[PDB]
Image (cartoon, rainbow, N blue to C red):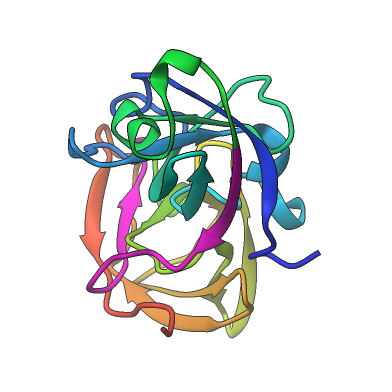
Amino acid sequence: MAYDDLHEGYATYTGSGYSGGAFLLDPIPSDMEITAINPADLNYGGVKAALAGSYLEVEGPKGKTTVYVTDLYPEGARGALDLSPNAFRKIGNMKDGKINIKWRVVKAPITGNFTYRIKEGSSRWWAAIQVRNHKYPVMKMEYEKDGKWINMEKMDYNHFVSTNLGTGSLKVRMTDIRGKVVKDTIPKLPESGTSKAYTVPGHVQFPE
């Protein structure tokens, strides 16, 4: 109904998600509080991986904490989260196995601008571009070509994808879950698909 509405569900805990999570957000600091998220809640607004790299404030029987969303919780029911143990311990008893929670999307406790990650295989012909360090969920990414703004499809693996992106620097614009839009420019994509993924610095952030 609204993006920041309270969700009721359950949480278990897991050690997965620090490395190899579905949203390709590595490296994740080993002491970060993180979660995997069920697929229905993940795909808010009909955007795949809408909530990938979002932060959630999660309340359990013992208190509240904030977690970075790094992975899919496969087959997870609506409302359900698979927390890292450092997060789970803060809000419940690990000996219970599974606890009732209430959670909502919150502003990222971060500083600085976006960083972009260009997936391996990317070029001006086909590219997958991830936004990192974003204050709110990224719902939309578009790039400019011949004076037109082209919408990029967000994929399950938390990158936006297009083909035939054109030449020169890539002018992009990002829309958050509140509908705030920021514009940035990324250097030229390679002329042949890259063998390795790489990151490039961004210069903008969603407003407070």
Assign the N terminus to one quadrant of the image.
Answer: bottom right
At 24% from the left and 38% from the top, the residue drawn is 28
Residue closest to the eye, 27 or 165: 27
Nearer to the camera, 157 or 164: 157
Please state if 28 lies on the left or on the right of 137 as rendered: left
Q: Residue at x 49, y 64 (%)?
A: 106
x then y, percent, for residue 22: 47, 30
- Extreme residue in the right direction: 1
Q: Residue furthest left?
A: 30
Q: Is residue 24 visible?
A: no
Reply yes or no: does residue 103 show up in magenta: yes
Q: Position of residue 66 (x, y in %)?
A: 39, 52
Q: Position of residue 141 (x, y in %)?
A: 55, 66
Q: Position of residue 65 (x, y in %)?
A: 39, 50
Looking at the image, residue 27 sits to the left or right of residue 169; the answer is left
Whether residue 140 is situated above or below residue 20 in the rendered picture: below
Left or right of 97 in this view: 113: left
Q: Is residue 191 above or below residue 194?
A: below
Q: Of residues 28 and 197, which is closer to you in this image? A: 28
195 above or below 41? above
Asked if the stretch drawn in magenta spans residue 186, the answer is no
Question: Could you tell me which residue is drawn at 72 percent across and 27 percent down?
Answer: 77
Res 171 visible: yes
Identify the magenta region: 101-120
User: Count the marks: how many?
Assistant: 0
* Quadrant of image for the C terminus: bottom left
Give residue 202's quadrant in the image.
bottom left
Residue at image location 61% in from the left, 21% down from the top: 74
